[PDB]
Length: 193
Length: 194
Length: 194
Ligand SMILES: CC(=O)SCCNC(=O)CCNC(=O)[C@@H](O)C(C)(C)COP(=O)(O)OP(=O)(O)OC[C@@H]1O[C@@H](n2cnc3c(N)ncnc32)[C@H](O)[C@@H]1OP(=O)(O)O
Ligand SMILES: CC(=O)SCCNC(=O)CCNC(=O)[C@@H](O)C(C)(C)COP(=O)(O)OP(=O)(O)OC[C@@H]1O[C@@H](n2cnc3c(N)ncnc32)[C@H](O)[C@@H]1OP(=O)(O)O
Ligand SMILES: CC(=O)SCCNC(=O)CCNC(=O)[C@H](O)C(C)(C)COP(=O)(O)OP(=O)(O)OC[C@H]1O[C@@H](n2cnc3c(N)ncnc32)[C@H](O)[C@@H]1OP(=O)(O)O
Image (cartoon, rainbow over all chains, first blue to last red; front, top):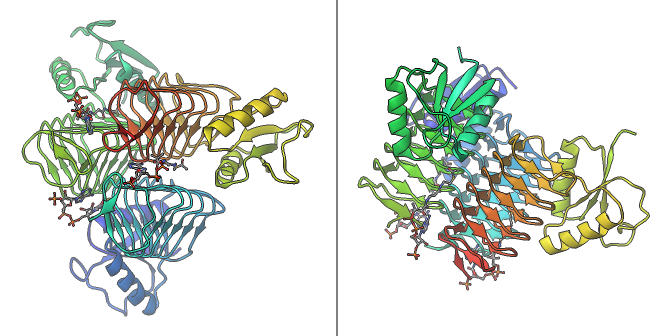
């Protein structure tokens, strides 16, 4: 790791990422935000980089842009996250792992994923690239979450289920059936909106 | 700074868990006070640190007031496993309970007399109003405003940018998806006025 | 005479997570057993500690009985990050699984063969009946009595002072708000008999 880190995103999401970065031992966070702070330039000095954008589509776009412009996009992983030695977390892939997250045996976390505070990824899950597993959201064993999915605060998915790319599981929702097409699912049990 | 002994007002279940937190913090001895079930509070007691171990928000506030008005220091009991952002604000010596594995993120503010129960989460920029109770596993998303004397039940949650009126109850397992500026009892997914 | 090896009965996903707990506790070698050629339980297996990593409550109980009756020790696998009150009672050498970041508060009792899965919470004074399974993130409020062989689904919860009949299922995401002394399957917020 370098001593400094760029945090793209001047917002509460950025601040939380900065806290994780400090936890990992980064000495200084340099914020950039083209809307809300200091504008990025492709001629900035090369330090470790992180994309603290909550929106999955925007995060992917900026990830591609920054990754093209030469920067290494590290993972920010809080020291209190518990990760099985047999779990797979893509290295240097802009993944955020917040405090008290647990990732169990043989689960796979793809690039650009957010695992937010106290979320749980059970054994043998696959969490697709640029997905956001929100605060307290829990995936049971063998759950496959598609690319760019959003699992809302305190939501959950029962074992052996799949959620299609680009889907939203609402805050508090309990998914009890496979979903092979994109949707927005809310309620206990979760149903299409 | 902390005294060797602490008086815990509340000889109950809530009292037992507070005692565990106090021991976690390093207190050597906990002395229970309870006006109905054991040793009585008296204004003449030595000035040891105090805590109000009463779950009921209204009663906790009444007792907090009585104790503080008698010149006793009501400390915070904060489990060592709680993770608190350096930019979060937790009111000092304000009878706040922070249970194990609680997380409080950047710029969140926790006011006097609040309970943050086991494994609750207070996300960035929240304000948790005085004498509120955020129950076990209850989670507030970013920029949530919880009113004074509110009660968020077990495993409940509030979506981002929302406000809950003073003196409201969010039921166990409830998911608040809309602002509520009129107090009430809200239950279900999504949370509806009862 | 160093204790290094453990048999884990159940070569499944549940087996893998049990192995990670055992290795967290400092076991060096995990020997999986299951009903497949070359790895079956046998009466004359060399004696090492056992654990039964079977999620199904009824089968777990049956295998527990068999291994126990062969004079073997069925240990508890308890992750070091679990927080257990000094006044809580967890039955010793009783095949109990306690996963990462579980909290068990003052005076709660955990009976033999129980599973407390990742990030579950057992509040003060609960009684969790033998061979019950409290799933990932499921939370029992204070003084809750869970019957034998119960299953509390992912992110379910039970409100304070409630009792759940032996052999019941609380569905994933369900919030139990009333006593159930007749067994059944209870789903939704609030939980209703299926
Ligand atoms: C910082 C972190 O990472 S943690 C928190 C992160 N964020 C979240 O969890 C937010 C997740 N988003 C949501 O839950 C949802 O509001 C969404 C995406 C399901 C729906 O969004 P929108 O379509 O904008 O819904 P909107 O607020 O306009 O409400 C339409 C409604 O559907 C209902 N509804 C909205 N969200 C939910 C929900 N989570 N559960 C149940 N019902 C819901 C509303 O009650 C309203 O119903 P009505 O027609 O009776 O008025
Ligand atoms: C130690 C800790 O911090 S963790 C645990 C802390 N404590 C809690 O979480 C308890 C929170 N309390 C509750 O959720 C609720 O029972 C309250 C406050 C919303 C309502 O309490 P009461 O008014 O006494 O409700 P009561 O039990 O009489 O039930 C009336 C009911 O509304 C329903 N109901 C009660 N609570 C809920 C709930 N949380 N969600 C959905 N429905 C509910 C009941 O099923 C019954 O409906 P019915 O008319 O169909 O029979
Ligand atoms: C590793 C861990 O320990 S974490 C994961 C642990 N495992 C779990 O949490 C699984 C818990 N199991 C469940 O919740 C269940 O689905 C049960 C036991 C409630 C029901 O199981 P089944 O009877 O097989 O339900 P099935 O999937 O056939 O669905 C029957 C229906 O009830 C509904 N349903 C199923 N589960 C639930 C639930 N948890 N909440 C609300 N409704 C539900 C379905 O939507 C369907 O309704 P429909 O008639 O409109 O189609």
